[PDB]
Image (cartoon, rainbow, N blue to C red; front, side, top):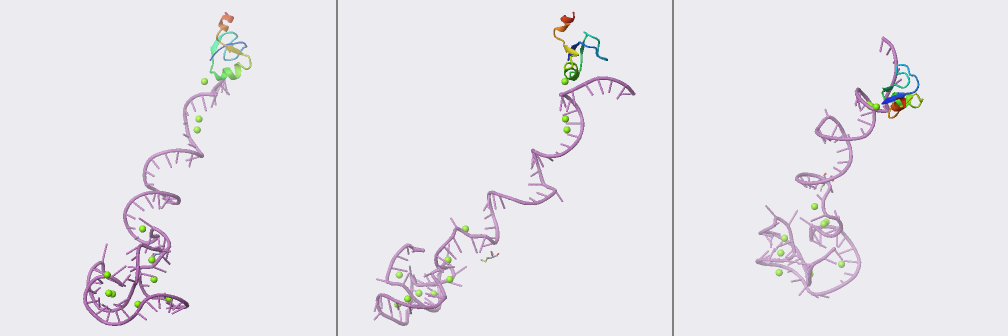
Amino acid sequence: MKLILTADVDHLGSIGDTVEVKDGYGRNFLLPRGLAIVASRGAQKQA
RNA sequence: UUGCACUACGAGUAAAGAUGCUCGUUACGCGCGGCAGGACGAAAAGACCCCGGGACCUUCACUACAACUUGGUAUUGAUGU
Ligand SMILES: *C(=O)[C@H](CCSC)NC=O
Ligand SMILES: [Mg+2]
Ligand SMILES: [Mg+2]
Ligand SMILES: [Mg+2]
Ligand SMILES: [Mg+2]
Ligand SMILES: [Mg+2]
Ligand SMILES: [Mg+2]
Ligand SMILES: [Mg+2]
Ligand SMILES: [Mg+2]
Ligand SMILES: [Mg+2]
Ligand SMILES: [Mg+2]
Ligand SMILES: [Mg+2]
């Protein structure tokens, strides 16, 4: 699943860049901790 | 229990062991008490045996299945080597 992240994650990206991740790292670690959101409209709220 | 009935015996004969058929012999009609030789006595659609069917049991008979177990894949991520 692809994510527009909000914090800084080592080995994954800086703020705001969209990146696809292995779908268990998304819903278990980056989404409950608030470090990312989905990529459906935030690319327009980043651009 | 019961097809009948004024239901003898001998030698025969016959589905090959006869109250009932042949040839003889014997026996007045009807009861009561006893005995248990026959009526292949009664009872039980022979348990034996065989044929057909069934059931349960056995196992290195056949096919399955539970259980137990093997790997892949999903749940399932991150980082070094
Ligand atoms: C033999 O096993 C025996 C014979 C019966 S005699 C008519 N049966 C026993 O049950
Ligand atoms: Mg997945
Ligand atoms: Mg005779
Ligand atoms: Mg005679
Ligand atoms: Mg006569
Ligand atoms: Mg007489
Ligand atoms: Mg008498
Ligand atoms: Mg007798
Ligand atoms: Mg009898
Ligand atoms: Mg019989
Ligand atoms: Mg397994
Ligand atoms: Mg498995």
